[PDB]
Length: 144
Length: 270
Image (cartoon, rainbow over all chains, first blue to last red; front, side):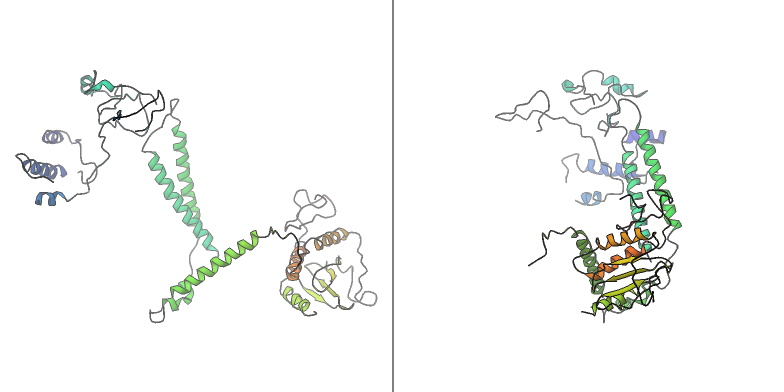
């Protein structure tokens, strides 16, 4: 957060709270996180005045985070039979849109990102993820 | 004071405008689901744009109408309801009003739809005629009269804008044995010696007479003679113009008229 803050000082188009009062929230965010840090580094408290003061939620709360994950084979002890078709029920540039608009490369760990990445200069991420991703044995592709 | 309809229309219009703009903004959250051929979503976009234009035009058209409301709202009628809580138990009044209106509308719709009855069969006073005549005579532009020189049977005539009076001599309750004439051609005041019948015309109103006879054999309800004669006189009133002639041109024949269903059209075609 401090390096992205110095970035924002170097260029005004940083990542804001995206909700309200975007143009000094970062200051109080940093303060609260440092508070929790100090209060939790060396066997500190957990989820009392700290809780009471952080209980205040300014008009800045975002939602809809990815939390990337994939289904599995929950064959516990007795029986779980699957067919060949009609399966039975059991980066940050989206990775979960409403409509499909590209090759829609699939992935196992969290990724679920684009295959060509449709960008110009983010090639660092693409290069680092050219090969199999983190445990990317399920790094597959799917149409539609 | 029928502005309530236009105001309900404006209500529906603003509700539809809100719904449309909300749906437009919601649809812009995502692009084409699976196009695979083109970017034809521009079509739906332009459709929503035109719907917005439609909404704006409707708002403008409704702003043009609904000029203004009258002063002194409620017309001092619910002042009792506007009164203090001392005399008001007041909402009960409006409740009963709404209940009565709803019950009336319900009964009307039920009676209307119940016209298709299921009764496979129907089995196990010189004072109503005058009352019915007085009730019917309250209607405007259609003057009636009666002399009854024959006896117990009823004899009466009706007048219209022209002098095309109609001679209807029927029984106590139901209308039958009628005849039509035009422009004093009957002169049934003292014709010959008295109010004569003569069952005749100059070979033009014979068609109108036949139509009226057919109507008499059509509106013959089993009971309620008041409704019968009301339907009869309404049927008669439909000839006050004799100018238009749908389903044809107004040159097909001598005349054009046969409205037993409350709508006239070119005769000799049904």
